Amino acid sequence: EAVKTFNSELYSLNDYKPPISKAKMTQITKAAIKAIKFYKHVVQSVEKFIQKCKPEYKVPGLYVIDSIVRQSRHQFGQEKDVFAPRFSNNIISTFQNLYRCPGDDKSKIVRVLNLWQKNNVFKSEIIQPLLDMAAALE
Amino acid sequence: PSYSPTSP
Image (cartoon, rainbow over all chains, first blue to last red; front, side):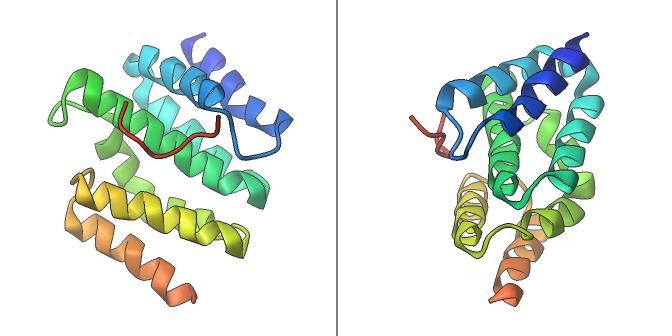
């Protein structure tokens, strides 16, 4: 039911034209965090959404990852956060999916990556390949 | 009103 509520709110993105509201992102994030016992399901659901969604929703999907990881690090501590480490497992493939976004959304992904790097959200060995993927597209 | 990748 925790996973059901999260999935419901995540897929509700399909009802809206991006950019997505702060309030909606907050709702999704709060549901993810409440469901921390099921963090593996939460990550799986986010990744599935990003794999399968329309191009206009790739950036919104990335923003869901960013929002969850940022709130989790804030709420539980950077060292104790379980979401960034779990998202890291498939992250190369997740980003391959994300970069299938409209060309005018590509700069938005790079922005997120640059901020993750600045804040050491992921190790360089993860961030650099993701940055390299954006550059190889140009 | 749109989400931005900012600190919570």
